[PDB]
Image: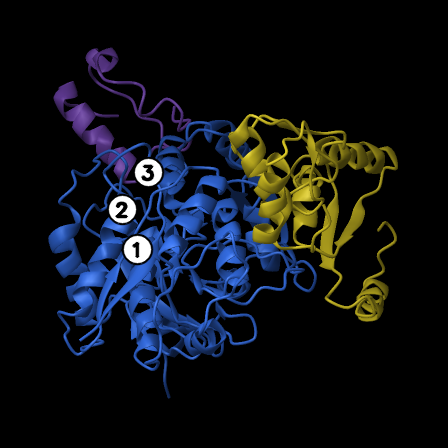
Amino acid sequence: THVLRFGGIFEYVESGPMGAEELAFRFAVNTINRNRTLLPNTTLTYDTQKINLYDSFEASKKACDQLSLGVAAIFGPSHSSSANAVQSICNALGVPHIQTRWKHQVSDNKDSFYVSLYPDFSSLSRAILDLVQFFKWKTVTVVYDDSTGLIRLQELIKAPSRYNLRLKIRQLPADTKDAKPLLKEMKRGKEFHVIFDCSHEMAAGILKQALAMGMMTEYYHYIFTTLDLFALDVEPYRYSGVNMTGFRILNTENTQVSSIIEKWSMERLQAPPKPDSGLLDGFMTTDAALMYDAVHVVSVAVQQFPQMTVSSLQCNRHKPWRFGTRFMSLIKEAHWEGLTGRITFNKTNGLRTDFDLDVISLKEEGLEKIGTWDPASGLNMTESQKGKP
Amino acid sequence: QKINLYDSFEASKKACDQLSLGVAAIFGPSHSSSANAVQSICNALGVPHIQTRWKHQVSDNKDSFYVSLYPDFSSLSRAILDLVQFFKWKTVTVVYDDSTGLIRLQELIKAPSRYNLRLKIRQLPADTKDAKPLLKEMKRGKEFHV
Amino acid sequence: IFDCSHEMAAGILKQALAMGMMTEYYHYIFTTLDLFALDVEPYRYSGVN
């Protein structure tokens, strides 16, 4: 017996197809009340917008726009620039802001009313470092994408602080085949342990090079910063014998997960795919899984709080919203168990710094879960118990 | 206009608010969480903008109405790299406090892939006092080019 | 050293690629002359002789 609206900001270039997460977002809207259990007497609606690449001023508008009505809580943009203002704004007006990307929060900022389902790297980069520290490498190359890659990995760069991993860092140029100058050195420096950092969009790009650069052998052992490792196309590679390694958080070990994905894959590709890119079009990418779970994680908090009503909140004013402080800290206890496994924000900072990474690797058959990681227990490698008394 | 450090929304107002009078070249906030916000406006409103600090430079923000008299870190980072290799040093230790110090110094961090060096990297924690252990380690570690 | 009409060469080569045998190590020699007719590009960087 109730309707409720969220906000929404997304990106595009002047038109559709809509932001594939937005397209996949409105889904998590609908799927709520078809698991009717979920917020039964409180039907959820929403509002969205679409904003610029490399901008927040427009996103400031669409922020203030979605604040004209006011919205119960905003799910936010892609760029940091776009999502840092949306952070402050909501957090200068009580509104909860939500995040699914990573972006380096300046550690001199006062803010509260934002959270980021994105699993932070101070764990990821710890996990990398564990994994590395297991394969007993005494060397590694860290290929990243752009400057901010560093700040993403600084746990790793600081492994020589304690550990004999004399590593080197190499940055990809603009294009994919802008790799060849780089890789050529690697093969000439003979750097047979490679950790990347780039959205998989460069992975397939960088990989087809590592193939055409004759670096797909048993020798090289590529490790990927990202999770969407699975989204790529195994097949061209799985025979060469290469060792490859990456993590996984879209916990496909659950039928429901493997159904919802499928139920989403039942609907996802109503847009035409892209063949050459090397992605398994039909595998719901992580970046969307969060924008999905968020909806649940977020709206489950609403399933604690009766008094909430969206309100017209103008940027002309200063007036913070009513129940933000009452509603915001509801979030930081939302221990939702969805696609990305356990979900529980580090209440100190409000970041998802606890989760289960299941390390996948490349056996000739495909991508095999071979070990499970968490912040707490380190690495359970299925290989660990390959001999018993 | 005087405002609080690290609040964009707050910082966003004065940008347009000044423009309610119109200004020629705003001289922006010196801390990127705000600086870009202003920058997000200046070329978005045709207005040129003048900046002093380095800021969390982004790859391809399509503004062009912003400059700064400040020397780009690349030149700086290259400049140290001139200096160190000049001093023939090998086992350097870079020491910062904030993550952005990396981007401040990547032109240097990348170099060992080209110039035979070694460089640990260490970070000053939240409090200033917290360096006493750092120095202690940097004492434990015998680092004589910092 | 192979022996097959190039029709198998491209076939056998795309394998030698997907079988991780396109390195500086292996040195493939072809019985046939139509070696040129194949498509160099996928290979010329791997360093193979």
Check the image and report above or below for A111 versus A89.
Answer: below
Three-letter code, disc 3 = Tyr
The local crowd at label 3, few if under 14, some if 14 to 19, many if 20 or more residues have their Cα within 10 Å, is some
Disc 1 and disc 2 in contact, CB within 8 angstroms: yes
* Residue that sits furthest to the front in the current view: B21
Residue for badge 1: A288
Residue for badge 2: A20
Residue for badge 3: A12
Examine the rendering and report whether any part of residue B57 can be seen. no
So how many labels did they put on this image? Answer: 3
The percent position of residue A197, horizontal first and vertical second, equals 48, 47
Q: In the depicted view, which residue is nearer to us: A299 or C15?
A: A299
Check the image and report above or below for A190 versus A111.
Answer: above
Looking at marks 2 and 3 on the same chain, the residue that comes earlier in the sequence is marked by: 3
Q: Which chain is yellow?
A: B
Q: Residue at x 73, y 59 (%)?
A: B123
**Tint applied to chain A in the drawing:** blue
Q: Residue at x 63, y 60 (%)?
A: A109
